[PDB]
Image: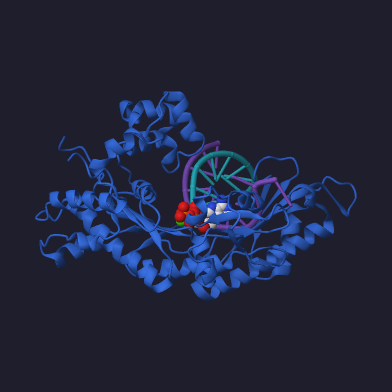
Chain colours: A blue, B purple, C cyan
DNA sequence: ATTATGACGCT
DNA sequence: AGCGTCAT
């Protein structure tokens, strides 16, 4: 009852860019705007692999991971932009730099956690408290929430989508008690007002549109964000959770999309997040471990405590390349040349990072895959990173992997390598 | 031949 | 430390 925590203490948003790499290319090349288009890497094999798709192209069934030649079968007029190639490999610098543009704007509003190249969590609890004081018990106008959906509404007592959106928003607002400065629903609503302002700033200052979720924690914020994309934001209230979760496949919740989620489904014989409420905390801990069990018990009730971490910059800087099929590296000279290519890109990025962010990496991690292993990585070895020098780093990487080679012949490399990976880690201030 | 990343958990 | 999971 009165002592039962409801996980309504925070206001958390997740802001996620719409079809991000496509928007970056569309800003650069106006011919691509408002077109079915996709971003591809490489080209020789089956037209290249698609890694981002405009909403116009999605209407034709084009998806990520599709080969461009196959996408063209669904969408003959599909336009394509290619990822830059440098030193023999795809180079994602343009998108990393565009990401920084967006993250720096968001950081003006609140402390952010960089969650990926195109999304960040926002802890808006303090910003909401301040805006609530400014408002002075003044009601929130629908005009302040022009792209906001209220999940679960309208209900009860209608043909167009925008019409439905406004209907739901009006029901929500009509209900709100603006007298209570600690009402969680009011706090979320003010959060949504701030996120409208954040999203407007991002679009004004970069040209990029985005979607957002506003709720009381990171998992619900992220779930919310995807409900109404693109170019819209969704508020998921604590009260909306039972209905929302009653038909929500377990795999849709962040961290449950893989083996653990499949095990929850199999072991418990359920399908939807809401069905988890019928198990005790101890029951869930017995199957999934102490940490997961406690997390699931709270999460299926809409409660999670994972903090928005104050981290705007990536913790690692890495360079990787696959060598599939017949292109697998089978000579020592090959392995060395590609280690150097990777190290040269890594040095470039590290040197820029040091100048921009006043820090230095101290550990180099080297990872490879060998033909036949189905695992992402076959072997991971670390060594000291003492100088930002590509020739040194590539020589050091070779040293820590060279024993991998089962070939008797010095020159030959066996089994061939199907992946190389260099990663700079363990930053220290400088 | 679903590539190039990046964070975090386990032991 | 080195490996595995989950994610975009
Ligand atoms: N599996 C991947 N491999 C390589 N790049 C990826 C992969 N997934 C995502 N990316 C890149 C390209 C995306 O534009 C960008 C952001 O990913 P993501 O948010 O999942 O989709 P998206 O921004 O392209 O479309 P959406 O509007 O559905 O969010 O990160
Ligand atoms: Ca996105
Ligand atoms: Mn994303």
Residue A127 is left or right of residue A62, and the answer is left
Nearer the observer, A49 or A403: A49
- Look at the image and tell me whether residue A388 can be seen: yes
Image vertical order of residue A50 relative to residue A199, above or below:
above
Q: Residue furthest bottom?
A: A355
* Number of numbered tags placed on the structure image: 0
Residue A62 is left or right of residue A392, and the answer is left
Quarter of the figure with residue A282 = top left
Percent from the top left, x then y, of residue A139? 13, 60
Percent from the top left, x then y, of residue C4? 58, 39
Q: Residue furthest right?
A: A409
Name the residue: 19% across, 39% down: A156
Q: Considering the image in quadrants, where does the N terminus of chain A appear?
A: top left
Nearer the observer, A323 or A298: A323
Image vertical order of residue A320 relative to residue A405, above or below:
below
Name the residue: 31% across, 50% down: A161
Nearer the observer, A211 or A194: A211
- Look at the image and tell me whether residue A107 can be seen: no
Quarter of the figure with residue A309 = bottom left
Residue A355 is left or right of residue A382, and the answer is left
Percent from the top left, x then y, of residue A61? 53, 47
């Amino acid at each position: 009852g009165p002592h039962m925590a409801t996980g309504q203490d925070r206001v958390v948003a997740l802001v996620d860019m719409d079809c991000f790499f496509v928007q970056v290319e569309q800003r650069q090349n106006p011919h691509l705007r408002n077109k079915p288009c996709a971003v591809v890497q490489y080209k020789s094999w089956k037209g290249g692999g698609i890694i981002a798709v405009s909403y116009e192209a999605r209407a034709f069934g084009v998806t990520r991971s599709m080969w461009a030649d196959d996408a063209k079968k669904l969408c003959p007029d599909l336009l394509l932009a290619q990822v830059r190639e440098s030193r023999g490999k795809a180079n994602l610098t343009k998108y990393r730099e565009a990401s920084v543009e967006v993250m720096e704007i968001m950081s003006r509003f609140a402390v952010i956690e960089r969650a990926s190249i195109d999304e960040a969590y926002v802890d808006l609890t303090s910003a909401v408290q301040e805006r609530l004081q400014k408002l002075q018990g003044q009601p929130i106008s629908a005009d302040l929430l022009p792209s906001t959906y209220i999940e679960g509404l309208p209900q009860g007592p209608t043909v167009q989508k925008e019409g439905m959106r406004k209907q739901g928003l009006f029901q929500w607002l009509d209900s709100l008690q603006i007298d209570n400065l600690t009402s969680p629903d009011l706090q979320l609503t003010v959060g949504a007002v701030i996120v409208e302002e954040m999203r407007a700033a991002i679009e004004r200052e970069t040209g990029f549109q985005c979607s957002a979720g506003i709720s009381h924690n990171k998992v619900l914020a992220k779930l919310a964000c995807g409900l109404n994309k693109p170019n819209r934001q969704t508020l998921v209230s604590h009260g909306s959770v039972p209905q929302l979760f009653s038909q929500m496949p377990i795999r849709k919740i962040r961290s449950l999309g893989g083996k653990l989620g499949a095990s929850v489904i199999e072991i418990l014989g359920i399908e939807y997040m809401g069905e988890l409420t019928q198990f005790t905390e101890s029951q869930l801990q017995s199957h999934f471990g102490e940490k997961n069990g406690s997390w699931l018990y709270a999460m299926c009730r809409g409660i999670e405590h994972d903090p928005v971490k104050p981290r705007q910059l990536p913790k690692t800087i890495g360079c990787s390349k696959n060598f599939p099929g017949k292109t697998a590296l089978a000579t020592r000279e090959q392995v060395q040349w590609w280690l150097l290519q990777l190290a040269q890109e890594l040095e470039e990025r590290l040197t820029k990072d040091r100048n921009d962010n006043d820090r230095v990496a101290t550990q180099l991690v080297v990872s490879i895959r060998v033909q036949g292993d189905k695992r992402l990585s076959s072997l991971r070895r670390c060594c000291a990173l003492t100088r930002y020098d590509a020739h040194k780093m590539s020589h050091d990487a070779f040293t820590v992997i060279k024993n991998c080679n089962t070939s008797g012949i010095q020159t030959e490399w066996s089994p061939p390598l199907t992946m190389l990976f260099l990663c700079a880690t363990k930053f220290s201030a400088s």
